[PDB]
Length: 294
Image 1 (cartoon, one colour):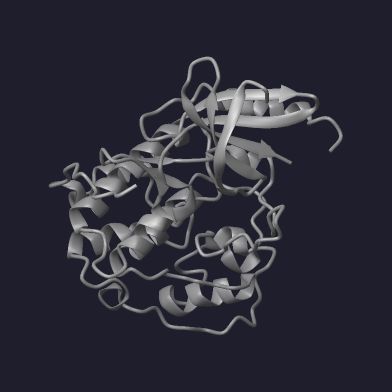
Image 2 (cartoon, helix red, strand yellow):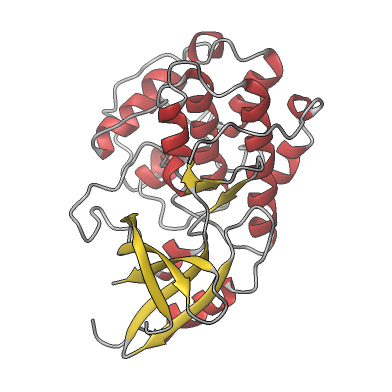
């Protein structure tokens, strides 16, 4: 809009270009996201308006929803870097465990908040986890997936990553529960620790099979009702579960215990954000300052 001066392009978003901009009135710097045409369905407008109310220290603040000239612009709080870039920058040495714990702890607080309001993300990934120089990490784009379905490709034709997608989604479950977000966060937790994506699938079946080879092909024992899901196939190969000691070294026993609970197949058995915050893994949690060189 005319009220904002585009400083620069932050990157390509799921729904449209993302710009760093300055409000010509408050002088504040923000993140402007254009959402991609008939006239914007009232459903999306109402949903997004509700998002302006779910405010939390670990949720990127939605400053304004600008709907003008039949176009949508979301104005968000600006943060200088995302977890994906931070992880890439810390490849040689890896994010210190204390910071990993702090980040997971804060992220769970964010999920617990949104989940308590029955709002889920559905597309959590390192790219939408933002951090600042003070040791904070925040979840970006929360609640947008429900307002605008998550596409296979972005407006730039970029392939939306499947790496953090929960198995119930891959198996065709039409109704998502807050458990999908815990799954994603579990995958992210494992990636920060090992410095390598847990399940880097490059297709839905490849993603599903990578999960199967690590956690074992799910059956009626560990996941009641799984064999009756839309995309389940009795012909799926049968792989045996691997031991977490092999999956995420050198994560200690508390970490492995919590990760296992965040990666449970049955969405109903998967640990909640609230319960995870009480896990012994966070007994010695602190808030370290990450070293960022902007």
